Image (cartoon, rainbow over all chains, first blue to last red; front, side, top):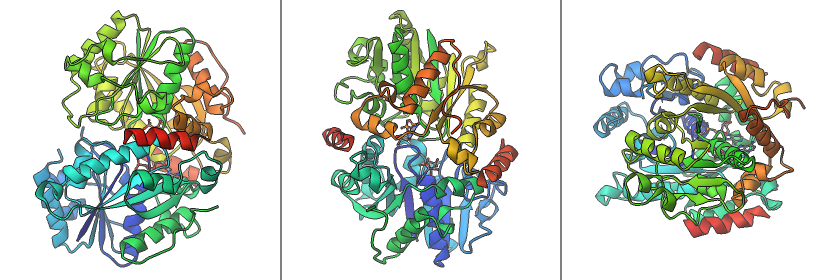
Length: 254
Length: 257
Length: 14
Length: 14
Ligand SMILES: Nc1ncnc2c1ncn2[C@@H]1O[C@H](COP(=O)(O)OP(=O)(O)O)[C@@H](O)[C@H]1O
Ligand SMILES: Nc1ncnc2c1ncn2[C@@H]1O[C@H](COP(=O)(O)OP(=O)(O)O)[C@@H](O)[C@H]1O
């Protein structure tokens, strides 16, 4: 099982959008996938996946033995192969607890465990990357987001379980998000290349600014399901790349 | 001194942009103002205010007695009357103590600050709780989007039960809605929650509406708060907000197309 | 018209 | 051209 954390440091860059689109895309491709909301006290993944009303038990309920993984997992209705473990709503997440949940999920034969991290570098975010095998560093072409992604790379290299044990390091990928090639050429926005020269890691996707993303969360339908959305297509490309297939980068020139 | 927390729950709605533009606007109006970054380990306020390289000591340095408030405060160079207390860069969740923050806020009142603008981080955990705990007012910063409206509601629940005023039966925190990244055209094509949809859900007084504006990215690129760009619609809407905070009515612009 | 769907889903939660 | 200013300010910090 590949445990993939979707992380960022900076708030509101597209972690939830990306965790949902990518988990769905993987499920579509027949890979049994669960996406877990690691947020502490805010439930946003269930809202974007459109299952906010089927949420009975959550991630912390399972850790404190008030519910089984089977009771808390919500099977997506729209896409086969896809499951959601939603976030607690108390103001809890223990290292031993999270480890136990992840082992149970491997035992249930999940191929991909997508960890939808919260913002920051404190508790919930640290917990989502700690057991990761890969990290999707989600970044906007903006100054706060590039600075906070760099800090998150520092933590991925020193505070993860792989770093703290001299194992093979977390495989890191840059997901450049809310890109606008026209803005870049008028000189108003950091380009894809500017961002690579600074956070020096492998590009795994570029998601264009797209009015489809607001419409997708409004309906609780991840944006990859909208087959006309450029953001959707770029997320389907990303999923291909995660599965080992080369795909040319679209939506980087105007 | 009015202690105003800029809060939201949801990440990336415009707290930093708003805390910066509003603190600047208040300063411009002659009110001595400090804006404090309450983030834990991530310094974004200094980057938006354009003083990322004059940061020697920070908020947690002052709390642990490694620096005085005078050593850590950065006087803005561009706008008279304006000061910035930047965020710590340690991962330690403890660092910001209730006793520590209180001591800093009293020192600031003693230095004659009229407005203490607290730029809160996302979440409801430690840094965010600390920013609202001593507030007299809260600017709930919200986008016309489903995650943001849900998370603002959760924050209203915290303002009403975990603030110092709520836990002591004092006059409750005065709440205002700053609706941000609005797009009237999107609203009329039926793609975006309208201003009124958002008020019917989070039932609090509107204090400003900031249009989606390409000037905001250009402003943070330069480290110059967007109110300083006199052609930017987002700047004008922030100058309106500041007027409303000072008690002047102003009609709401940029809500119709 | 997805703003209307958003509004209804929101009211049920809040 | 503010993208260039952003890029220089960024490199100094990181
Ligand atoms: N490609 C995109 N185009 C336009 N808006 C986007 C895009 N990706 C995300 N957004 C918007 O950005 C905001 C942040 O998205 P979200 O996934 O909630 O951020 P995070 O999970 O990092 O907090 C949302 O309001 C969403 O509509
Ligand atoms: N009125 C606006 N128009 C366009 N973009 C905006 C506006 N307000 C904020 N943004 C953008 O939204 C993102 C989040 O802003 P920021 O103030 O950093 O969020 P927060 O401080 O709430 O975490 C930034 O990339 C910023 O450039």
